[PDB]
Amino acid sequence: TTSASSHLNKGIKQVYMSLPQGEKVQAMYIWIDGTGEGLRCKTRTLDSEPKCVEELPEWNFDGSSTLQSEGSNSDMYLVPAAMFRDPFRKDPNKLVLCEVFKYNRRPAETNLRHTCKRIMDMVSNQHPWFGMEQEYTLMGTDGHPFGWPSNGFPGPQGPYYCGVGADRAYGRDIVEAHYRACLYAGVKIAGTNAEVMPAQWEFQIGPCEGISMGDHLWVARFILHRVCEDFGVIATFDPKPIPGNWNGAGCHTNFSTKAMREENGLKYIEEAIEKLSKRHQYHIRAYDPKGGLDNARRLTGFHETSNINDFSAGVANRSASIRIPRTVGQEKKGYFEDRRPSANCDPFSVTEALIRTCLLNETGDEPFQYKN
Amino acid sequence: TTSASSHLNKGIKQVYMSLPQGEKVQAMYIWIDGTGEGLRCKTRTLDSEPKCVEELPEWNFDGSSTLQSEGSNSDMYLVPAAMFRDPFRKDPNKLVLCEVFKYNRRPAETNLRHTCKRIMDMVSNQHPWFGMEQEYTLMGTDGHPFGWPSNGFPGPQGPYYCGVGADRAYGRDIVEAHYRACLYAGVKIAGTNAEVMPAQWEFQIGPCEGISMGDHLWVARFILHRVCEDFGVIATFDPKPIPGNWNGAGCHTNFSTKAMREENGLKYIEEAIEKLSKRHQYHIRAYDPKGGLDNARRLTGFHETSNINDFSAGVANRSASIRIPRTVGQEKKGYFEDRRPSANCDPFSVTEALIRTCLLNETGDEPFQYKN
Amino acid sequence: TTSASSHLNKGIKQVYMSLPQGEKVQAMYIWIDGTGEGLRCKTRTLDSEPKCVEELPEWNFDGSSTLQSEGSNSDMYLVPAAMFRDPFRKDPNKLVLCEVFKYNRRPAETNLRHTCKRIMDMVSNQHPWFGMEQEYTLMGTDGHPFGWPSNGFPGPQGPYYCGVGADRAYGRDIVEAHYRACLYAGVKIAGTNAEVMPAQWEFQIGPCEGISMGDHLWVARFILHRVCEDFGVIATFDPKPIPGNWNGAGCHTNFSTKAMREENGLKYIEEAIEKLSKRHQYHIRAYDPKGGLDNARRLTGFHETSNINDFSAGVANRSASIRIPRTVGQEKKGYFEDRRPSANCDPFSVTEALIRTCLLNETGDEPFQYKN
Amino acid sequence: TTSASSHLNKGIKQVYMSLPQGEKVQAMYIWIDGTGEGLRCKTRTLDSEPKCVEELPEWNFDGSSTLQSEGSNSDMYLVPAAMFRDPFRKDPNKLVLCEVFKYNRRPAETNLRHTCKRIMDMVSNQHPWFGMEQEYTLMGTDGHPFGWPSNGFPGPQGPYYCGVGADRAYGRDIVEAHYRACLYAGVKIAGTNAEVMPAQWEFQIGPCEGISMGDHLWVARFILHRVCEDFGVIATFDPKPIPGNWNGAGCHTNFSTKAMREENGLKYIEEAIEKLSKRHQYHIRAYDPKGGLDNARRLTGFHETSNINDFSAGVANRSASIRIPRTVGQEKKGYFEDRRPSANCDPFSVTEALIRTCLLNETGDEPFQYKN
Amino acid sequence: TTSASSHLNKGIKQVYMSLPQGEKVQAMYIWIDGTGEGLRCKTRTLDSEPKCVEELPEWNFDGSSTLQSEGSNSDMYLVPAAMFRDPFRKDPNKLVLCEVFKYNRRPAETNLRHTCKRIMDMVSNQHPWFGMEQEYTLMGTDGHPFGWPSNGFPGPQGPYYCGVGADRAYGRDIVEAHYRACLYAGVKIAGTNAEVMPAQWEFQIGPCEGISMGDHLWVARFILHRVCEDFGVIATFDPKPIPGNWNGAGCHTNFSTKAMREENGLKYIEEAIEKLSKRHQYHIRAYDPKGGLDNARRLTGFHETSNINDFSAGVANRSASIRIPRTVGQEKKGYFEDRRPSANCDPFSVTEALIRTCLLNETGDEPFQYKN
Ligand SMILES: Nc1ncnc2c1ncn2[C@@H]1O[C@H](COP(=O)(O)OP(=O)(O)OP(=O)(O)O)[C@@H](O)[C@H]1O
Ligand SMILES: Nc1ncnc2c1ncn2[C@@H]1O[C@H](COP(=O)(O)OP(=O)(O)OP(=O)(O)O)[C@@H](O)[C@H]1O
Ligand SMILES: Nc1ncnc2c1ncn2[C@@H]1O[C@H](COP(=O)(O)OP(=O)(O)OP(=O)(O)O)[C@@H](O)[C@H]1O
Ligand SMILES: Nc1ncnc2c1ncn2[C@@H]1O[C@H](COP(=O)(O)OP(=O)(O)OP(=O)(O)O)[C@@H](O)[C@H]1O
Ligand SMILES: Nc1ncnc2c1ncn2[C@@H]1O[C@H](COP(=O)(O)OP(=O)(O)OP(=O)(O)O)[C@@H](O)[C@H]1O
Ligand SMILES: [Mg+2]
Ligand SMILES: [Mg+2]
Ligand SMILES: [Mg+2]
Ligand SMILES: [Mg+2]
Ligand SMILES: [Mg+2]
Ligand SMILES: [Mg+2]
Ligand SMILES: [Mg+2]
Ligand SMILES: [Mg+2]
Ligand SMILES: [Mg+2]
Ligand SMILES: [Mg+2]
């Protein structure tokens, strides 16, 4: 059920990591590969501790081993974008998230931060805040959910949501370790809870301003994969890991601006929802790395989900595409929640689409090539 | 056998838990679900350490995943009531027990603290003290008592009560860990002992004044479930876990007022017992989350138990419904013990009934609405 | 071969035991049950650390669960007698050895300390010293000696006495842990050695003055049982655990008075041995909880043992019932050793008989009712 | 999951069973014990093969060991009633079903065949025919259904009914062996099929005239238990072995007389249905060995069943209490089916109640005396 | 739990055992060893099949290896007494039960057949008949009953007597093989049944006239041990294999003569029982190979047993020392049953004591030392 690497003696490893480091510093570079969903990493040694992200040098990798580059001109380039403390090696070592560029310095096909950053800079005075709810499922190496009966199923759903106890919550050791690692690293983690499906979990990131939302979620995803690797289990972001009467996985996105958060900001919330109602197909394509096919296995209109074909909005409606919390409606200010994005969405795509539709008043089925 | 989660490498988890936290603080919210027996929890991040319960924010959860609300209006609200230190994450993180309210702010069906608190405030000058003896059995994930022979039975009862040794006491590691965690958290745990059935244990909570009795017992129950989850075993509060000639599980409740604790207070003890003798059926219904059916499997008048049908009382009588300790009768002051409540009773329901019958002079089969 | 409780993750338990305790203090009460050989225990919480044994309150327990009372009037009472530091929970927690009294305050049937203490007060000016050598065998949960071949036997005796090495000494981890725990608790442990039988061991307690010999040996027995519970093995004091050509288990008792320890004290040693020669049957009955039946399986006159029904004494004779060490005989002062008591003897019975015969000049087959 | 006896080398047994018997003949005596549900057996040696049941001698057993008598007059007696060929020992050995009588030669409490034979003799010319469909569940020795995932569940119902394949039929080896064993013995087995719940099966016995129905069903149950003993699994007749969304087990009874089998015999069925409608409570009590404490957990009105408190009828209605097959109504001739009795019913009780209600026109809550 | 030899491939052995033997004949010699309750065997080759026991040659063995002699005149001799067909090697191979004689041609100490045969010849004209019920317990090689839970107990007694099913009968494969093996060999086996304790069984031998009773029972015991050797389990004849509330094992002896079997033979039974009442202590000593130190742990006066120190008799009284069947009393002819002998009794000793007291009118303490 668990990997062979996780059966090695971990006490031996801790003895080596107790050795004082000395003067050199380790930096781990992290980037998104050609599938748009996977992460890659490698480590270099630095002479001294970097104080800001601008002090880190550019790097490179062979793009033919990541299905990102052609044959002859295979070299790709890494440009640091955000820096965090490394929870796996501790201070003064760092984690570095990078943008990917081709040999001719054009952005890579899966490099979506480059365009999203420019869009964020166009509306910086409105101070957009984002909050994302990442759902995932812990799986054994055999392709079955962790802690499930072998070749079988646990009891029916209902007691597992926010559950406590040996027979209710599976794999809380991973969840606790991931929570503390994110806090140490500097990732803005807001909370966690157990989900309807046993061995299914959720963590919230935010509220984050502008481009930082995508950076924090991607690094949080990397930390989860690396923590699960220590325990020998697999975390999956597939929207429908188990077919049938078992809960799916999504990534709800909460959105607000400076105008929405002030008194009588509910008026501006309703304006944005009206604009979103006219671009349902555009956001479905942008909320999936495959264009909507992945989300079709999840958004069928059952198990507290909305239909993939129809747009709906309402106050305190958890079955609609867009939900206004009851407290927000009562206080006439706050935010609203988009429940359409799938659990494997790219945050840079999702946040860029929301700004384009709601703040830049874009129409049609294509993004505006220059600005808005 | 134990759960798959308990076979993960716990040394790995402690490495992550050793990371310094930083400035943010974790708060775990805890509430009682729609069955009136189970507990639920989830965690949010706070900006700074809360000093009192009054400065924690309200929260919410989806009640359709806990069988507490219907479809359209499913949002429920959490209101903090009592705060303790978190033994699983250590200072400055907190545990928060909450009351549950519906979407229209009316109390939930299983929210019995709201009415119990008002009753306790009616008799605050009499200073009621409660002491509760919680019995439970440790279970394997296969539904059999922990440490019992597979598909079989251990030796006859008699050597397991207050026992010591590998062949006499099963699961003392859980008991020791639970005791220390409660002391750290601030729960008023008074003692523990091994019970007549092997793998059966007991811990005592009190003496607690007023509404704080229910708060301390529920948090103690939560800590036990969470501790057992680490070891991979299940703690059950079922009154009769094993049929036949094996000891059952109850929750004895000790009761005293300021008048009973003073000299010649035995007179007021005798008066309260007389009032209790006239309301046997009312207390049987209130001492069970199912109206008394659960307690029928345990209270059959055998193995040092009282009859479910009959009321009896006496000094130093462990076979009666109400027992006056021999010391209390000798010093003519003290308290008395109600031995009827089952091990899965709700403390808020049990304590409210005692106040209504003994201090508010209520009669009939229904509680008196507003005042007494 | 070992218990299910011992396969739980002990690292998890140590995390909880690392939590700072706070202001409250745990006290474990220990007493002897109705079989005269087994120990019982339970824990209560105190508000502050007790400084002397007189500050601890009286307690009680249900005697019908320990075969010490039946029917009505089954409550028993515990009176603290001696206090030690708790090695399992560390300072400021305490272990408390108690005397048992029935509901009418008469001493219980197996409470032999009450009479033994009064006898020791009658000879206080002679300062009797006692030293006892407790032998025991470590056993697996399957009823076979620990580390022995399954359904088989190890090699013949001879290399195991005071042995070192994986093939010579079984279970030294328990012996080392028990030694350190006794030193921490304050028990006057004098040494240990491996015995002729593999997995058989011995520890020495003393020299102890008066009634303190019984208190120290009983607490050492409890500590041994509790330590073995941690490792998942059973320690047995049965005189002949394995039938045939395998070493038995005894409890040799060394005795001396102030006159015996002074120069030319060998004269008073010979006087006491002369008195002992006339009361062989009386001491055989008092050296066993069954009146001598258990010791019959051991004292057959083989394997360096004396005959059960014959009395003998000599200098440097290890086959006699009473042995005078050669050093003592050469220096004309010291002590002497009684080799008759079985390994499961009650120390209060053994010490009381020695005082009555040697210092109070009692005759007949019954103890003198009043003083002397 | 399987018994220790099933892990013995079965090839060794087959060698001994191939030895020629000689001239002696074995005979196995079977009778119903004091619970009214289980069976008991023992073997004796006869000098020659009996040609009919009337040549078998009487026997006896100890009734105190079977919970059928006290210690004063414990002896009970066995009178053979029906003979069958032995499928476990082959010819010329026999199985004999016996009636149980007290020491005073009066029928035992669970001996329901005596009165049923007397009742059935009174309607001989009508030639009543019976056919019963017996359902059962195969269980491992751990108390879980055989082949189910450990501490878990298989997929939801729907593919298991009459299924074929490793993932659809659990334990067909037992079913095939039982079918062939019954045919060899002379049991009138009509067919088998796999049931809705996995590891649940059904066999049909009949049409058997008169008292012969109870003899054939009881022997078939004994053969099933004995066959399952060879494989090491347990056959259970519980009405609801698994709680929840899983099918229960019943024993449908098919009834017809000569009149209903003749031309236009459908009209004689209608009076039988009409007569049965007024005695629903009386028949429910006689359809359960525990008076209704078992069938109450199956007849819940769901899973295509009928409610325990309501009587229904109709042509080709499987949800009613009584079903008339569609072909029977089309041909206006045949039988009708009673779906009320549980799987653990006594066939003698069921057949007697049907005869005395539809053929003797009995009323009231008590069986008629010599008047009927 | 089973022997290493039983895990060898038994299919390989059956291949060799199917080879045609040829003209040589195997004969196995069986005799009782120096302990008086164990058996020994040895095999030799004969030129042709013996037609009767009288043409089997005498043999010999080493008595020092069997502890029936010292190292000076260790040689002993075997004289054939009874011949049986070999069930383990099939025809024409044979089993031979032999008497043991010293080097000086005098009977061995445990050779009780020699004197018993002379006693039977004295009263041969009355044709005494004997029938013995031999009880035994099946054990694993670890010293625990076969099929019992590891280091534990099954459910309480009551369903195991004459039970059927995987959870009620333990090890019926051995019982079925032994029954068929005895019939093939010519042993007069009368029947079998399961006993009160699980894994405990019984078989009956008789009615056997005179000296043949001891021959048939001893061969039956040998066949059981040899059959159990094939399966890898141990059959024990200990009177009290498991201490506590678990049934013991005895060897009930049924006795009758021609007068008792004739008309009005009940009056002759009363004389024998009256004569038996006087020599209770004499028979108790002769009913135990250890003189009474084995049967003392069974005849406790509980679990339907008679106290070893009390003689009692009565019609159909299973708690008495002597039982008269109810049918015998009603028919005034038959036999009577002696319930005193233990399971490990010597049939020659038991049958000789019954003849001496009831038929020869002997009295006193020691047997008559001359023929007349
Ligand atoms: N003003 C805001 N602007 C943007 N995001 C916000 C704002 N306020 C809160 N959020 C984010 O909204 C999210 C709240 O989601 P949470 O999981 O706590 O509740 P929920 O949506 O009611 O739950 P569920 O999982 O049942 O849908 C968090 O990620 C938080 O950071
Ligand atoms: N004055 C008091 N008022 C209320 N509760 C009290 C008072 N004094 C003590 N108690 C409570 O009474 C309980 C004592 O019960 P404990 O389990 O120690 O003994 P017991 O009832 O005699 O034992 P058993 O488990 O055999 O019934 C504790 O929970 C304690 O807090
Ligand atoms: N003066 C004394 N009075 C009483 N006891 C004493 C005195 N001096 C020593 N002792 C005790 O005598 C005991 C000696 O036991 P020890 O195991 O050393 O004996 P040993 O001679 O090696 O014998 P063995 O081979 O039987 O174990 C110790 O318990 C010690 O405390
Ligand atoms: N005339 C008859 N009288 C009595 N019993 C009959 C008669 N004809 C057939 N039977 C019996 O009725 C039974 C028919 O059961 P069967 O399970 O085959 O029917 P069904 O309608 O498919 O049942 P199910 O409720 O399981 O779907 C058989 O045992 C058969 O012997
Ligand atoms: N006339 C007789 N003389 C001697 N033995 C006889 C006679 N008739 C029968 N027997 C033998 O008596 C034995 C009866 O044993 P069986 O177990 O059937 O008796 P039971 O009364 O049921 O006793 P229990 O309940 O104590 O086992 C058989 O071995 C049988 O051969
Ligand atoms: Mg959420
Ligand atoms: Mg959400
Ligand atoms: Mg208590
Ligand atoms: Mg109590
Ligand atoms: Mg020593
Ligand atoms: Mg010594
Ligand atoms: Mg059918
Ligand atoms: Mg049917
Ligand atoms: Mg018998
Ligand atoms: Mg008998």
Image (cartoon, coloured by chain):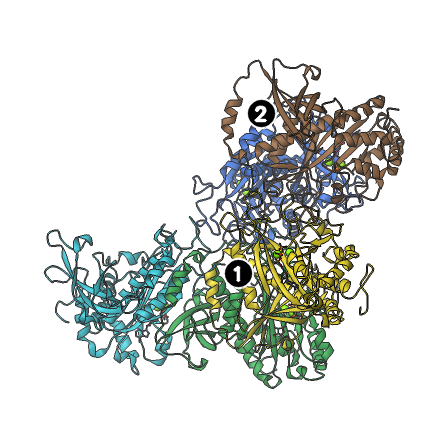
Chain colours: A cyan, B green, C yellow, D blue, E brown
**Which residue type carries mark 2?**
Ser
Q: Residue furthest bottom?
A: B125
Residue displayed at 82% across by 59% down: C365
Between E328 and A288, the one lying in front of the other is: E328
Relative image position of residue A360 (x, y in whole percent)? 18, 73
Relative image position of residue A231 (x, y in whole percent)? 37, 57
Between A278 and A154, the one lying in front of the other is: A154
SS for dot 1: helix
Q: Are marks 2 and 1 in contact (CB under 8 Å)?
A: no
| Marks 2 and 1 on same chain | no
Q: Which residue is mark 2?
A: D18
Residue displayed at 76% across by 50% down: C310
Relative image position of residue A201 (x, y in whole percent)? 38, 62
Ligand 15 appears in which quadrant?
A: top right
Q: Is residue D325 left or right of residue B92?
A: right
Q: Is residue A135 visible?
A: yes
Q: Kindly indicate the quadrant of the structure image that contains residue A272.
A: bottom left
Marks 2 and 1, how far apart in space? Answer: 61 Å
C179 versus B60 height, above or below: above
Relative image position of residue D236 (x, y in whole percent)? 58, 45
Task: Rate crowding at label 1 as few (under 14), some (14 to 19) or many (20 or more) other CA atoms within 10 Å.
Answer: some
Q: Kindly indicate the quadrant of the structure image that contains residue E3.
A: top right
Label 1, ligand 10: CB separation under 8 Å: no
SS for dot 2: loop
Task: Rate crowding at label 2 as few (under 14), some (14 to 19) or many (20 or more) other CA atoms within 10 Å.
Answer: few
**Which residue type carries mark 1?**
Ala
Q: Which residue is mark 1?
A: C177
Q: Is residue A73 left or right of residue E236?
A: left
Q: Kindly indicate the quadrant of the structure image that contains residue A247.
A: bottom left
Chain ID at mark 2: D
Q: Nearer the viewer, mark 2 or mark 1?
A: 1
